[PDB]
Amino acid sequence: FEQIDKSGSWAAIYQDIRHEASDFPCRVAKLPKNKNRNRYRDVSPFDHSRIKLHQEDNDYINASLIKMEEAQRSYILTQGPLPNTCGHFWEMVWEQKSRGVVMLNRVMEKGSLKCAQYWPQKEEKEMIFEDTNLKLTLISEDIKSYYTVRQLELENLTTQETREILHFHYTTWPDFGVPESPASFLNFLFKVRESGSLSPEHGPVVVHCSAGIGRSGTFCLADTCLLLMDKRKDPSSVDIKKVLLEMRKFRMGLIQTADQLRFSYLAVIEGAKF
Amino acid sequence: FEQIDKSGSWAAIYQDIRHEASDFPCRVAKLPKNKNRNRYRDVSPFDHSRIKLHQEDNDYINASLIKMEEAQRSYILTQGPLPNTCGHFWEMVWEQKSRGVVMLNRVMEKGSLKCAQYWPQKEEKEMIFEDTNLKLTLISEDIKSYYTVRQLELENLTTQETREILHFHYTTWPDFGVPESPASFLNFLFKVRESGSLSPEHGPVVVHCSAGIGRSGTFCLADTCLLLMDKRKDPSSVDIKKVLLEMRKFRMGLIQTADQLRFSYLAVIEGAKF
Amino acid sequence: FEQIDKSGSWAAIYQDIRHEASDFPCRVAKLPKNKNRNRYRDVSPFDHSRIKLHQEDNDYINASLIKMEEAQRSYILTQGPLPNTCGHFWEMVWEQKSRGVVMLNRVMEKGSLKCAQYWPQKEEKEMIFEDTNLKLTLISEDIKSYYTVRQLELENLTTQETREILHFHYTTWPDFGVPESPASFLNFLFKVRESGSLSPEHGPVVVHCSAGIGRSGTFCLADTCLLLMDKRKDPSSVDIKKVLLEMRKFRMGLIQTADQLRFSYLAVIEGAKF
Amino acid sequence: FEQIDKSGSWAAIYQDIRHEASDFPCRVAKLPKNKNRNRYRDVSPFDHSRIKLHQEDNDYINASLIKMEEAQRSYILTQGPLPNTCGHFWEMVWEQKSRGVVMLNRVMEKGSLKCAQYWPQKEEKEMIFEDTNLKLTLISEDIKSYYTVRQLELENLTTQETREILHFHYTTWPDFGVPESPASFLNFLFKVRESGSLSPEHGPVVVHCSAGIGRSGTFCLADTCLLLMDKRKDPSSVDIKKVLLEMRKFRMGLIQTADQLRFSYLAVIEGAKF
Ligand SMILES: [Ca+2]
Ligand SMILES: [Ca+2]
Ligand SMILES: [Ca+2]
Ligand SMILES: [Ca+2]
């Protein structure tokens, strides 16, 4: 980390990542009928790793399955739900048997609006996604300094089945740049790990920010490298650049700035001492 | 055949069929509570011949019992199971004591998911349908060039009784149109017949495709006409038009198009030679 | 055709072919050091037409260049790659600047592994052939009822140059005998032709099956005879027997049996109608 | 553990395992031509999980791939090599990219003979498996009280490639019954874990005793439960009986006596305190 900051090789390094990143088709994501299902034109799931909704009509949702073979962890990265894809977002959660949903953004950042209000803010004001026939209810919530955790009850109206989804909401990511310290970010991840949401019995955790590649990518990149740094007889054979590129084979654009790159390094380093 | 072909009157023959097609109530199927159990709104089982689930909550499944008196053969035509009807699907196979299941479509065609993955792809990852208390295990899988035959074990979790179900999967019917030649399709049929799945000792074979009327209708129409010709002293007296209409009394829309109609006559003809 | 068929003289025609078949040295192929590079002892490339690897250690690969002068089309016939020849296989595709690879067999038939998994099944798990310094990546995969077309990226790791290879995989040739109808086989051919893979702008298409002479021979014989008939003012003057023998000068044993011979005449005939 | 020893419910429990164990075909293992490739008639790999040798002629070897999805670990269980399957055993190691081979028996136990001498006992007396063209050399060995560890160099003569295989040989398993204390057994496993042989970068570790189900099964059952007991938010949701049954879906007869069962429990318990 020393040399790179000194010789200021962050932009260089990050740029070499963008250049080396794999390229795969996103045919489906580009179909005209799926334009309003994408939040950003420049952010699409590859055809090979995209999550297919279990429907005949339109199985399209902007979400990717990231399977890290060696680190032994799967993640579903997706965009913040759109006002019209909230039911799709929750149908995905259900079909993929996810236990936890990790949100890394605020429903409103800067003067724009980065994500829809896809979960109920009020216990008594539950949500019913008629398109996908699902019911979602806020059971309780624990609000903290840098993150909030909610207990949501998701119900398959078609089968009256119910499941409890843990919603981990990191709420203090700055409108600009990355956090000066990976402090809270790392604590947040440990909470997610300790919750059991990232274990094999469950479907992959659903991770999202606005586009589902920058913040989301840091979360997964960090978690994965930390797994590696602890799952390898060698304490440093793990190269986060290489890891990120592996990760990029599954979803385009993971880590959208040299800052996010530097931060990811910070987190892995500052987290390896945990 | 050559006449109809030369005069190009299939379409005409086909429309007269649609005209004479019997018409019966489909009250249960159209009940609001069954809306999610139907794949297609224009394809429902007549009340009088629909298969009833031996359950009190909801006995409905989009499946029809087609009992052909002269040919002495019964078939159950149904739609490709939906995500929420896989359990209902197997409860029917169980309750009806079927021995074979004929799948005439691939899980994915023309992009659309035309059928849920209602059976286990992996021997070691059996399926449990909790709503219907059945367990399903893939025992064996013999993949051939134009079809795959699987050997499955269905077990009623309450009684612990187990049965071997043979799953015949015709895998090469084109995404568009009908086969140019009926050879492989007939060999598939003969193969289904050889297994004894169609035997009167067993409940009706369960046949399905996308809606359970086109390819499915073709399979049973061909089979039944071959049974008649082989049985009737005058193989020529076998009017397949009359056979179809007779079948159309049990499930609506059997044979969706002219080409499918043409393919059926040919199949019976080529099959006639055995 | 009907004559030969009615007189039942295919076998006879076939043996005369085996009699007139030219005979050339296969010295290199038979060298002790190449023993492990040959799938079958009775199938070797003549020295004069064998494909030479642009390497000094060992330039041998069981592959033959079949250049047909009149039809103006060249083919490379080779055996299904062995575990140790996948790298050699791709170095040839690269060096020879081929655009398409035609696979006419399934990886597993009649139980036996008739071909190594020489290409990546997973977009995210590319293949590296260290002995030949090439990287191979599955880019796309369009699975159809009777064949699968893949889009692959081959990259010389030394030069970083990349090329798109189209892999046409005819997947429904029966484990035993030949197709009853040549329809799907011809459509496959036409599909191969449409891709421009056979274009003179490209190096020879690489064709292969188990030994690289039966199904492979059928594909190129049919294709070449269709080229002649379409070109020659007298489509009848096209003697496929003479065409085959002409091809047999470049690689031994093209067309392994009478039935394959019969299937070839039919294919050309049915294909003749276009 | 208390209650079961008291109420002496070991035989009961073990018996319920044998009764509940899955049953899958072993067609290939039963082919007449593979009789001398099996050490025990009653011990065969299931067709679905058997390791296929990468050859066209005969891909049969009595070895199974055990994939524990949740515990996130794969193992290849196989019989002690036979005088004629030593090359097959080593070809498997190579093709499957295994890094370590765990041997739980002595080449001679009691008055019989439980396994072949498939590795070289002398640095200067290396081994050449001509059938599969492999060279194996003892590079060094570390002999201990209850186990020995060897550094072997395996070379693909066909490609001159070489790899270093770690051979972990637990040498103090008693001729009868199980070890009174899981002490050494647990230490042995930790050595294997610490060696990195059980990590994801490598192919699955190859585990064997004589038949490859009793001792081998204890090793894997113990390792897997220990992973679970540490990978689950819950410190006891892990039921070794359930785990063993899961494991049995991949290889028949894992854990061949109620003693081995009790011992496996001992090991998991006595090992959970590590
Ligand atoms: Ca995929
Ligand atoms: Ca009735
Ligand atoms: Ca030459
Ligand atoms: Ca398997």
Image (tube, coloured by chain):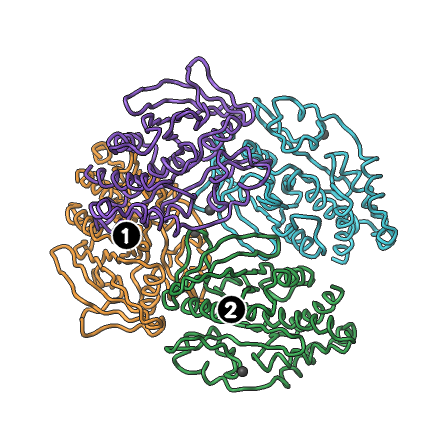
Chain colours: A purple, B cyan, C green, D orange
Q: Are the residues under marks 2 and 1 on the same chain?
A: no
Front one among A218 and C207: A218
Front one among A68 and B116: A68
Q: Which residue is mark 1?
A: D216
The label shown at residue C126 is none
The x and y percentages for residue D104 are 23, 56
In this picture, residue A99 sits left or right of residue B103: left
Kind of residue at badge 1:
Ser
Residue D112 seen from this side: yes
Q: For the residue labelled by badge 1, is the local secondary structure a helix, a strand or a loop?
A: helix
Question: In the figure, residue D225 lies in which quadrant?
Answer: top left
Q: Quadrant of the N terminus of chain A?
A: top left
State the residue at coordinates (49%, 28%). A82
The x and y percentages for residue D30 are 44, 60
- In space, the residues marked 2 and 1 are separated at their CA atoms by 51 Å
Ligand 3, what quadrant? bottom right
| Residue neighbourhood size for the residue with mark 1, other residues' Cα within 10 Å, grouped as few (<14), some (14–19), many (≥20) | many
The x and y percentages for residue D55 are 43, 66
* Chain label for disc 1: D
Q: Which residue is mark 2?
A: C97
Whether A80 is drawn above or below A228: the answer is: above
Kind of residue at badge 2:
Lys
